[PDB]
Image (cartoon, rainbow, N blue to C red; front, side, top):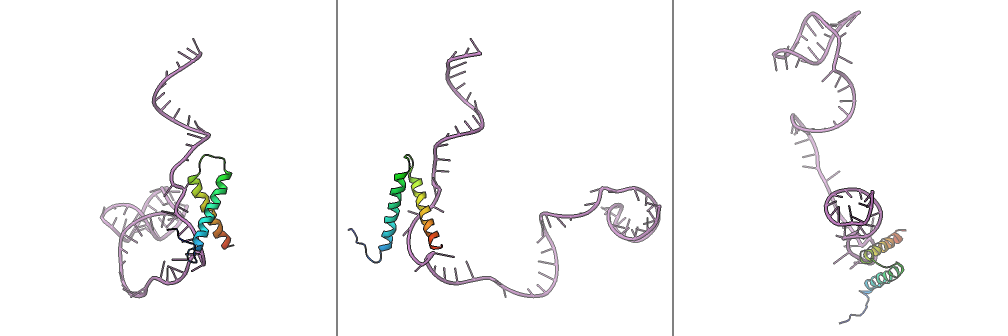
Length: 56
RNA sequence: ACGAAUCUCUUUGCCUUUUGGCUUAGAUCAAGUGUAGUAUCUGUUCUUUUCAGUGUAACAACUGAA
């Protein structure tokens, strides 16, 4: 049961694709060894930064 | 003195959930009064000269002059 993207669940999907898309880049930049806690932390910086953009 | 093992200690290094997501911050909402009375923290001043009176269980405290 793969559920299509519709009006109600649009912007949730937009979130999900954005978060993945950022982890891809930043993980492809860093040298190597440790990610996952670091992976989690980077995304919190993202969302915080978006909130800052809305509030100017 | 030296190859050199083990326990103790400092440092460098290593590090743990180093917040689960999303939207219109997702939205909205919040403290009674009066009369009498006690308890308990902190701050500030004094252990500093004699004698005479008031005072006190005794001090203390208060009141005068060298």
